[PDB]
Every structure is written in structure tokens, then in C-alpha cells.
Image: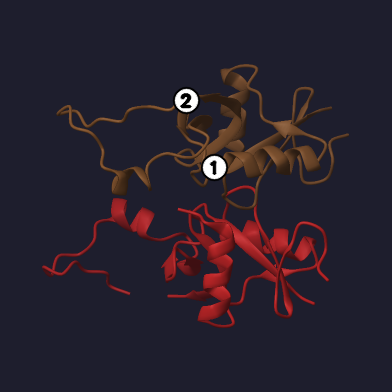
Chain colours: A red, B brown
Amino acid sequence: ECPQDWLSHRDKCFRVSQVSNTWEEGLVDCDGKGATLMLIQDQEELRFLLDSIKEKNSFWIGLRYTLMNWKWINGSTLNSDVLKITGDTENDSCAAISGDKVTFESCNSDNRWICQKEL
Amino acid sequence: ECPQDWLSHRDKCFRVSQVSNTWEEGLVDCDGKGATLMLIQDQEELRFLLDSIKEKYNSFWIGLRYTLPDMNWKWINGSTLNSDVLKITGDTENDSCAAISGDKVTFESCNSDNRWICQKEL
């Protein structure tokens, strides 16, 4: 059995954050619960979760990497004001669940997150 | 002195729900936590929570509800809703429930799926 107030599914306990915040704040929140950011095991896991949650925000998952001449489809370069909010100082890219898909965005965006524990 | 994982503000504690579900499910969820669905003292209190949650477009059930009589539902053109549409219109309880949505309180059918805020008084 899982701890109180954690969703159960197969071998895993899940917890969904109360608040929205950076990818890093979600990861440090999870560690503090002795958990980690959700690592999607399969389509069935994800849909189950989303069925229980019924959200209509994104959720940060345990995926991050570090990314370039950015151009629009017409050939013109992205000006800096746009670069500002397409990305961040660190030029990292952090993954979130937004419905049944995995989107990628600046780690400084505010989303909710899911923490997981292996029972 | 607020329980762990409750948000602290003046002499109140708040907890936002992990999940979205009916107004009644939130009512009962909070009761099981020794709390009630949020009762708003003032706008400051509403803004604190929003600035905490950082989700100013979602809807949050609070502790306010009314019911209606059973209604003869017509379209704006004056014609009657046929039974096949009435089967998926509104809810059994003919109720409407209050929800925070940004700096406002709107009413929505009580069978919608929204997150909720429970409050305890600290």
C-alpha cells in the first residue's frame, strides 16, 4: 500500500503538486518526499494518471536536456525578445505532460508536477 | 501550526486538491480532512491563494451552492429542448456551485470537474 494521499497504480505511488512552479522546484519538492519526478513507464500509466487527475495545466516529468541559430519558417531569425521567452539563461529544455502528449519548454515555466515512488 | 502541506495565511490554513472532480466530492474530501471547502473572507485572501498556486485561469470549487426548481428549458428562439438533449443537460440535483476563477467567483454546474480548496482555521 501507498502513503496517505498518494494515487496507487501497479508498483507505483503518485503525488500531484498543489501549486505551479519551475521544473527544478518540482524536482526538489519530489526529493523532499523521498520521491522523484514522474518517469512515464507506458501509455497505460499516463492515461490512468490523467484519468484520475482530469486536468484541463501541464505536468513536469523527469526529463531534461540542454539544447543553435533559431529561424522562423520564412528564413528570418528569431529576435531576442522572443528568444527570451522561447528559452532560458541555461538553454535547458524540460519535459511536461500536457494531455496525452509530452511537450518541451523552458525549465523556468510554471507547471504542476507529478512525483512518483516505487512501492 | 498548520498541518504539513497546507498553505498558511492569516489565521487560516488552505490545501488545494491534487485532482479535479465534482463539487460534492470536494465537499466530502475536505470534511474527511477536518476542514471545509473554502469560505472567502475577502479579495486579499483570494489573491494570496492565486499568487501561491500560480494558476490564475483554473477554477477552484469553494463552499457556496444553490439549487433551482426543475425547469422548462427552452432555447433562445423559444423552442423546447427535446428529451434526447435534456439527458445530457445540467445535473440531477439542479444545482449550481461557486468556483474561484481568477479574481472572481462564478457559478458552474455542480457536476463539472474542478480542483477545490479546503480551509482550516488555525
Query: How many numbered discs, if any?
Result: 2
Compared across the picture, whether A70 is left or right of B116 comes to: left
Residue A77 visible, this orientation: yes
Please determine whether, in this image, residue B68 is positioned above or below residue A57: above
- Answer whether residue A63 is visible to the viewer in this image: no
Badge 1 local density, few (<14 within 10 Å), some, or many (20+)?
A: some
Determine the image quadrant of residue B44. Answer: top right
Return the x and y of residue A106 as percentages of the image width and height: 45, 61
Secondary structure, mark 1, is loop
Ranked by sequence position, the earlier of labels 1 and 2 is 1
Which residue is labeled 2 in the image? Answer: B104
Instruction: Please provide percent x and percent y for residue A12.
Output: 72, 75
Residue indicated by mark 1: B54
Rendered residue at 51%/80% (across/down): A43
Label 2 sits on a secondary structure element that is strand
Q: Position of residue A79 (x, y in %)?
A: 24, 56
Q: Position of residue B30 (x, y in %)?
A: 73, 39
Pick out the residue farthest to the top: B42
Kindly report which numbered mark, 1 or 2, lies closer to the viewer in this rendering.
Answer: 2
Q: Residue at x 37, y 47 (%)?
A: B87
